[PDB]
Image (cartoon, rainbow, N blue to C red):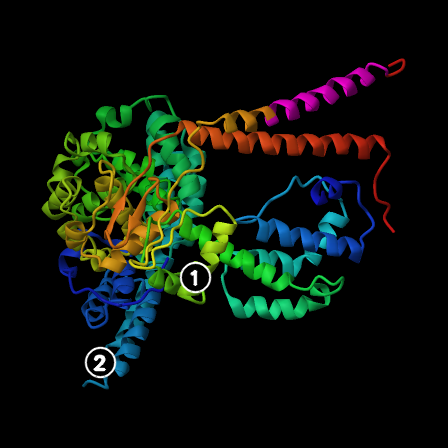
Amino acid sequence: KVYIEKDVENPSLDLEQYAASYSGLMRIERLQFIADHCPTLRVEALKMALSFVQRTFNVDMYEEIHRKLSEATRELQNAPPALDTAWVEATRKKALLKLEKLDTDLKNYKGNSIKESIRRGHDDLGDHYLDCGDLSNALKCYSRARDYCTSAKHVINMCLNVIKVSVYLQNWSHVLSYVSKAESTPEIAEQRGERDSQTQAILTKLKCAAGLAELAARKYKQAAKCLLLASFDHCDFPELLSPSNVAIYGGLCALATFDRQELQRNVISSSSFKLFLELEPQVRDIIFKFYESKYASCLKMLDEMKDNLLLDMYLAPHVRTLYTQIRNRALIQYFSPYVSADMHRMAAAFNTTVAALEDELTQLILEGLISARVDSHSKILYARDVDQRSTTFEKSLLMGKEFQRRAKAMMLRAAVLRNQIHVKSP
Amino acid sequence: FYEQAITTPAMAVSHIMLESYKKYILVSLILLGKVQQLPKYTSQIVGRFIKPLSNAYHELAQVYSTNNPSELRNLVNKHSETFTRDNNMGLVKQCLSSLYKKNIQRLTKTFLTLSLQDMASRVQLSGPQEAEKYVLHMIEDGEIFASINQKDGMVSFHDNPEKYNNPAMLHNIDQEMLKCIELDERLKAMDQEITVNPQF
């Protein structure tokens, strides 16, 4: 899931504390990806990534990464690499034989012939598939794992382990169906209330999953419906989301989706999200004075975090969508009360050139809601008109005319039918 | 007339009927501000066979959204075989007329007034003075909310379709009256004759 993507680069990261934040597969994943449109900071991102290949050692990705490494290294050599690849191959064989170790273990445990032994077999199998960074047959065990779960804790096991799989499995339809299930389906109220007002809400993980869903699914309504639902007391998942990204992600899905009232309720009266609230003071007062309409610097930091949402692997894929609806609803926000859109100071605010301003507006014309027109020499709109009654009149007459049109059409149609009329094939 | 007769059970295709659907295209696209979509209860093989035969015509329908002189020129040269196949000289600039239809119609609900020199710059219009020239023939078209400001170069919209305030309104509606009247009259007459159906 890489979008080409231009640069392109933003120096606004700190990857040490990112790996502090995230981990596992996704760690080096985004390391790579960001490095791609973040050259020369590509450097250390990929360095620490490959050292993470020195961490449980998926060295196929080592291959890929040092591949890129020497590629961009020689490409660097315009400007101005030295690596222990052979010892890497030695430890590679080490890893593969450890694979074989745990495989023999696996088959032993197959031989154990115990349903809960079966379940832990699934567990540790997928575990080491995670470990050395090759994951495939792991799914089978979890693909098999549901056949060994009957009880409520068995439901717990099936659900949390399938989805903990999905952390790097990362597949919506079935796993979103199981989010719906594990929250609702088995033992309604789940027989555990999701941990009875779930102390550590894996509900939170469910939430992250469906949120990325309606990221791609783009039905961001329920997305923000969960985004608001952030429950800190789950308190830990490095693959879950950085609380910076947690809050920004969620609240900005909302800031796309919302209508202002319930969202201010969602925002100004947000309580469950209040830590998540208090995460980014930036985005906090961003949306604050946004709804308060300091459009200038709001949009400013908006398309300043342009580059860093780009720096998000997952904010990149919808930057156009976001900024689109952002300036759309910026319009929607300020424009609604007025009657004749003056631009001069207002353009001084939005920081769009007079032509670019009015062509934003011209865009607006393409869809806009107000029966509005402009003396360009006014440099100022007048907004929507008044009457809807006569509007009804004109639509009424259009109605009647096409009615009579259809009516004659069908008269003549009764003729053509009942006059046997048709067309032969030759 | 076209559409009401073309939903007729059709299995024989004719280049005559090809001229038919072509000219229908001509109207339905030019005559309209955008494309019409029809009650698709026309022929099985014909309406769906000439439909790919309308390859250039669906693409030119897209062209109605395109606003490019050169491409339409090329397609016109293509179909000139039809452009003059029955002394139908002028169909291409009929298309060009639909073009400036789109131009002006866009311009309609945009604003009140612009630098109409600059607007002619805007709308791919070929001549500012010329611009008011075809504007004013739209005035002969009797539709436009425009106006003649030599001095300030001002053309405004004036948004008076109707003020619901007429014995004229009465006339529109009495038209509607008698029209719908005789409409329902033959409704009842044909119903009447349906009463004449035999043992059933």
Q: For mark 2, name the chain.
A: A
User: Against A37, is B195 above or below?
Assistant: above
Q: Main secondary structure of the magenta part?
A: helix
**Residue shown at the point (81%, 18%) measured from the top left:** B194
Neighbours of disc 2 within 10 Å: few (<14), some (14-19), many (20+):
few
- Left or right of residue A386: residue B142: right
Q: Nearer the viewer, residue B178 or B15?
A: B178
Rendering quarter of residue A20: bottom left
Callout 1 secondary element: helix
Callout 1 environment at 10 Å: few (<14), some (14 to 19), or many (20+)?
Answer: some
- From the image, tell me which residue sits under label 1: B131
Q: For this rendering, which residue is in front, A93 or A55?
A: A55
The amino acid pointed to by label 2 is: Ala
Element at badge 2? loop
Q: Which residue is nearer to you in this view: A66 or B125?
A: B125
Residue A200 visible at all: yes
| Residue under label 2 | A82
Q: CA distance from mark 1 to mark 2?
A: 70 Å
The quadrant of the image that shows the N terminus of chain A is: bottom left
Q: Is residue A20 visible?
A: no
Work out whether disc 1 and disc 2 sit on a shared chain: no
Q: Which disc is residue A415 wearing? A: none
Task: Tell me the subunit letter for badge 1.
Answer: B
Discs 1/2, front: 1
Across and down, in percent, residue A415 comes to 80, 32
**Residue segment shown in magenta:** B175-196
